[PDB]
Image 1: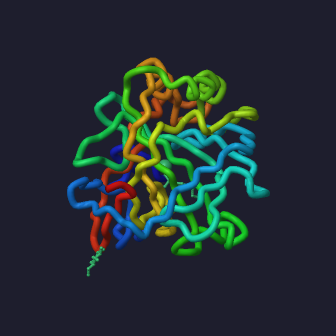
Image 2 (image 1 turned 60 degrees about the horizontal axis):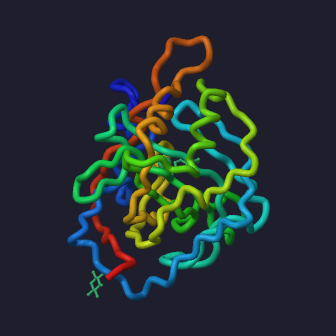
Length: 257
Ligand SMILES: CCCCc1ccc(S(N)(=O)=O)cc1
Ligand SMILES: OC[C@H]1O[C@@H](O)[C@H](O)[C@@H](O)[C@@H]1O
Ligand SMILES: [Zn+2]
């Protein structure tokens, strides 16, 4: 099956997922000079006060922190979005070294990691129906650089030892995703896709300009996870990022002048 290695990584995905060569694939390089301020963007609203986290899962590609999305609790609205998008999960992509790991790049610069907060458009009822729609999903992307520790990340870091291998999960209630945000909500936005198979072209991307800082020790613990299952040969979960894809017939808009 698909993965990130030489034999099953991003350059192979198109064989089983031909949309990998499509017209609105993600991630992309964000050329900051060409991105244009868009006065039609409404204020962005990240409303996570009532978020209900449930569980953390190693799915063999990353780890997902899952939320109860059975009601409007944690939601994203405003900005480029029409209507209400409900938080379902977050996960990260990261590197083997601090010099790589992000999926989006900024003037070609790669960050150490990238956080994706995944939301679905409530007008479509369920995530599965949302991924049949061209405006089904909104992903809030946040870059990570290595410097000072992020206190709100430490609870995630400390549970990773309990989900080392593919298929393991752990209770992860009462986690507040507000502790993963930077100060500023300045962002870039463009229409794109999921960055892993099935690569579906459903996503409004909202990528924050301000990175969060995490410590070297925090990211080193991400890199102790395993792609493999229990009892199988150890393959460190590192470099689980897709490189930038062709921009094609798209424009990146900025929320800030
Ligand atoms: C049909 C299940 C799809 C799950 C999925 C959700 C989000 C992303 S990402 N990396 O944020 O674009 C990738 C995959
Ligand atoms: O025709 C002019 C228009 O061109 C578009 O490509 C830009 O997105 C708009 O901001 C601009 O007003
Ligand atoms: Zn992702």
